Image (cartoon, coloured by chain):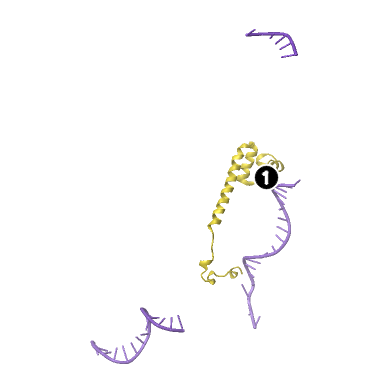
Chain colours: A yellow, B purple
DNA sequence: CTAGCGACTAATTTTTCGGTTCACGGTCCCACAACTAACGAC
């Protein structure tokens, strides 16, 4: 059904002339947004060393395994509730 | 030079769709393959 719901681009005469188009402005804007996000993350990384060591390691682990309160709690010693509160 | 003074996170369950199975009365032009009628040799 899906493959029979798909037409052929040849049904439109000279489809390569007026269809299947893109604007590089969109690509440049997407890359600019990516750069903005990267700059924000670099700002956060630079702020990280100013925090307490335990809270810095909590975030560092949460950024390389990922908000895994259970596995972090067993790793740390604090419970699920305490570890979530500290995060 | 010194002293007195003004509720969030993890674990378990349950359900719709896809997979599988059964299987009787137009034109003009340029090449290419047949092809055949005539021509020459044994």
| Residue A79 placement (x, y as % from top left) | 70, 41
| Residue A24 placement (x, y as % from top left) | 53, 57
Q: Quadrant of residue A50?
A: top right
Q: Is residue A76 left or right of residue B33?
A: right
Pick the residue in front: A74 or A52: A52
**Kind of element beneath mark 1:** helix
Q: In which quarter of the image is residue B13?
A: bottom right
Q: Which quadrant of the figure contains the N terminus of chain A?
A: bottom right
Q: In which quarter of the image is residue B6?
A: top right
Question: On what subunit does the disc labeled 1 rest?
Answer: A
Q: Is residue B29 left or right of residue A83?
A: left
Q: Which residue is drawn at 59% across and 42% down?
A: A43
Pick the residue in front: A84 or B30: B30
Q: Which quadrant of the figure contains the C terminus of chain A?
A: top right
Q: Residue at x 66, y 44 (%)?
A: A71
Pick the residue in front: B17 or B5: B5
Is A28 placed above or below A15 here?
above
Is A70 placed above or below B40 here?
above
Q: Is residue A71 left or right of residue B31?
A: right
Q: Which residue is drawn at 56% across and 48% down?
A: A35
Q: Name the residue under label 1.
A: A69
| Residue A65 placement (x, y as % from top left) | 62, 46
| Residue A11 placement (x, y as % from top left) | 54, 72
């Amino acid at each position: 059904k899906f493959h029979k719901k798909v037409n052929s681009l040849e049904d439109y005469d000279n489809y390569q002339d007026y269809m299947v188009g893109y604007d590089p402005v969109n690509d440049s804007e997407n890359l600019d947004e990516q750069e903005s996000t990267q700059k924000s993350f670099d700002h956060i990384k630079s702020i990280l060393p100013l925090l307490n060591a335990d809270k810095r390691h909590l975030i560092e682990l949460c950024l390389k395994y990922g908000f895994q309160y259970k596995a972090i709690s067993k790793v740390m010693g604090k419970g699920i509730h305490e570890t979530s509160r500290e995060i």
